[PDB]
Length: 272
Ligand SMILES: O=C(Nc1ccc(Oc2ccncc2)cc1)Nc1cccc(C(F)(F)F)c1
Image (cartoon, rainbow, N blue to C red; front, top):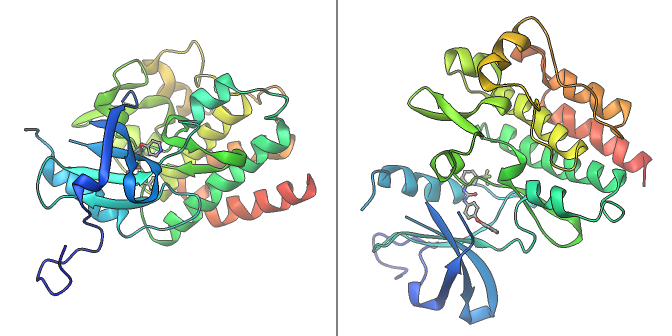
């Protein structure tokens, strides 16, 4: 826009500057090119019932910056249809990736690195007192040299699979949702820690669906009296001990991300 103008927004960019394309199977995200720089990018778009919510996401994205969080390049919220441009992550989402990778190339060390990256992003978000709400591998993205960034798709309605079910005013990744949050709709950074713990598990197992076989309805009950996923084949003892600490029934017991990242750094440096 216009610098002197009263509504100047650095992030608002020319909608013509982006050569929209086809969908990256998802709201809806297509893949786009930013002609100016010949760079492929991710464009998230929206007569729908969540405008206050979209622009909110835009707004937030404008406040966060970190090497391990998907990067917002610009927006298009001056005139509809509403856009949201972020860098593209050639490898798509962490969960499929883990399911279609060459495990010789994606060994234990690499998997330990991915967790370290993710933990680092969460430490930031924790420092900025920001609550993710839906941390999980389907929500992390994969780039070159095993670069992993944390994101948010708003998979809630995009998905209905069996991943998400109704609790509160909507759907919730039951298997990723912490106790307190399933029972009181209490979401905190400690709730994200829980989910992280699960995401770890997703990582340890190259992308296997959590609490396999178990039905959503019974998840809480089990966790209630202290039941947990078992260490996955190949997972180091120290990693696993970590998951458990994340999975403590009392939020205040769960380690901070600052602590979680400090533990990984020490492990990832000891292994490379
Ligand atoms: O991530 C967000 N939007 C988004 C847009 C496009 C996407 O698609 C895609 C992009 C790149 N490469 C491939 C695909 C994926 C996610 N929004 C968001 C809201 C709140 C918090 C965060 C976080 F803390 F995680 F950073 C992010």
